[PDB]
Amino acid sequence: STNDNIKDLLDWYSSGSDTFTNSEVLDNSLGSMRIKNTDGSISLIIFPSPYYSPAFTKGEKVDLNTKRTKKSQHTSEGTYIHFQISGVTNTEKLPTPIELPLKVKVHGKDSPLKYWPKFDKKQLAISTLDFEIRHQLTKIHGLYRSSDKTGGYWKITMNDGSTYQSDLSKKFEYNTEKPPINIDEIKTIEAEIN
């Protein structure tokens, strides 16, 4: 059986995200941005980490592969609003959608992929990658769904030596998160479960 901490993580990781494209920067202030989405909804997004501090000016276009911090709401003027965290990248696309090299090992034994699509964006926020990764892990492999599957790590080995990783037991550290990366420069992605 799982501990209460685990459940909370499962919920977080099995509740999809909010993909938006070509949204407009309305306001950018320390810690957050007000961005007008294509469907006319307004997204209020927070960036807790001082390392990843969005610098687009009021007027620029940006993409969003983010998550909701709490239930979305309606304003007095009838506008729908979303409260999200991280996930704001520039608009540059890739000449051709590429598959990100993902490898998974459930308790040592390798396990072939499934919900693994390709991407079209030049850059992606690490949080985004984290939840994509974790999402497949949970949905497909059984992460957080059983006592014997409550931990591990995902490691992103870059083309230029640099590395990225997170503990599959703690909620991604949004507060210390590093800037977005160019997925075509990713060398490999590894994931392990215990």
Image (cartoon, grey):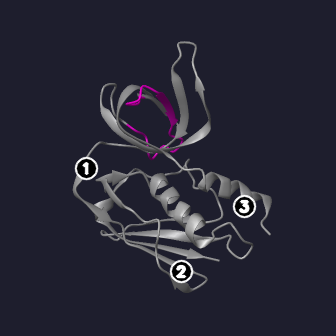
Query: Does dot 1 land on a helix, a strand or a loop?
Result: strand
Gap in angstroms between the C-alphas marked 3 and 2:
20 Å
Quarter location, residue 109: bottom right
In percent of width and height, residue 180 lies at: 38, 51
Residue 30 makes an appearance in the image:
no
State the residue at coordinates (51%, 47%). 17
Query: Does dot 3 land on a helix, a strand or a loop?
Result: helix
Q: Residue furthest top?
A: 77
Q: Which amino acid does label 1 sit on?
A: Lys
In percent of width and height, residue 4 lies at: 79, 58
- Upstream in the sequence, badge 1 or badge 3? 3
Q: Residue furthest left?
A: 95
Gap in angstroms between the C-alphas marked 1 and 3:
36 Å
Q: In this view, does 84 lie to the left or right of 91?
A: right
Q: Residue 105 carries which label?
A: 2
Q: Which amino acid does label 3 sit on?
A: Ile
